[PDB]
Image (tube, rainbow, N blue to C red):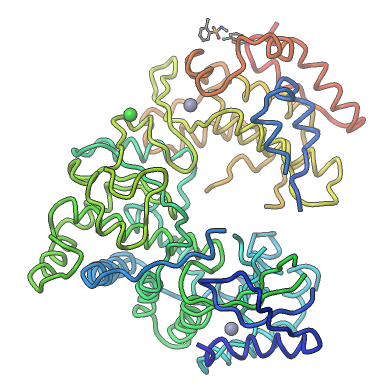
Length: 571
Ligand SMILES: CNS(=O)(=O)c1ccccc1Cl
Ligand SMILES: CNS(=O)(=O)c1ccccc1Cl
Ligand SMILES: [Cl-]
Ligand SMILES: [Zn+2]
Ligand SMILES: [Zn+2]
């Protein structure tokens, strides 16, 4: 407690000694309060909006640009649950770490991430200026030697829920735990259940492969506030990755887990305006990319235990018998890898095809681990899916699409209002017309490679690419990102969907976009197309006028028409 978190608080208290007041009317119940001291909207992308006029009247799209679960506690699991988790976590770190060696990530790797503008969750006005200043690295090394001493001084979170930190503390986490993402621990090759690095164009093929396994329904239960339901027992099972480490790495990693995760300190603004300095032991508080890997790990653990419950491996969560323990251990060594293969897990998001539908009502371990299901009553059996093309995963569903030549594409899809509404939004200040145009181009190229099968998005993508100068490079201030490039989109399409695609045996290239199919006209409408509306027909007819409006605003530049690629603009 105060041994570990004190110095961090005491250092903050000193710097605001003239304004340090113990607020007696503090709203916290489950967070520990310590003291208080005196102390960013969505912006519309104009290029994308001018080329999507029909959507200017559609509520869902328009309203996307307009505009307390942290203060809950999580009961400690029973003895049987805690034993199931410890055994499963032990086994899972071994299976993951069999083909992978834990290592420290380097200043040089970290600096490359800041120079390439990667999201680290920092709070020198820029990351670039800090990694170039040798002073900072002296601050880092001071904390570093404090961590080797088993102590902490400057690793405090800043809730604004994304918890930001000073770049230093971010480096110390990346140095100790970055290997999990940097070395692809949660790849489908190393993990069997994971999809890390897969890409949207892979995920449908993966869920079709899971479908092929004999068993029951596909389950895709969402957890009600996953990050808030991470227990101290969860954090202790995650910490066992240090059992596979040695030297400066093992001790440094041990310090991230014990000083920053298993104990924390946070600064949250309250408008009554005072900064509160609060602490707690449990719940997920770490960088997004580490949080992704540890969420995947604990989700993989939880779903193997739910599978064990459905299969009758153990009878009660109250207490595991020594005989139950060896059976659990034997199930893992015998069938564990096959069971991990029956799942697709992306952080808190899962799809599970269990051995049979007993899984649907195997709820005692899942509820006792704190992973309570969203939108369903505590003890009501899960609703399963009887077709892989209906299963929700990573905010998508997936269609099976037949090319005129008989080859099979499995494509990603979601309601089209969501896609158009997101592409119309840009975050942050000081965007030039050129910067705004290059972000619109990034969305257009993504639609050409991921959503080419939606009539409205292939047309709007061709319009935006025709309105932005051909040689201007697509941008994104903040999954694979193959659409990010200046190469021909047809060349990239052929690479992604034909050349690289392990599910496509015939490698015969496509030589025209008209060889690339759409969903059925009725299916397109079901997934939110405006085909059949008068607004959409006038937009399609008159698209060159919209393109020319945006060209006139950007000015005299090198422009390439990409509308002739489509049959209806081809003479
Ligand atoms: C607007 N005409 S359409 O797109 O061909 C169509 C879509 C869905 C159901 C019936 C029809 Cl006719
Ligand atoms: C050529 N345009 S379109 O997207 O094929 C279409 C537009 C309006 C109604 C139905 C359809 Cl299919
Ligand atoms: Cl279904
Ligand atoms: Zn620290
Ligand atoms: Zn769809």
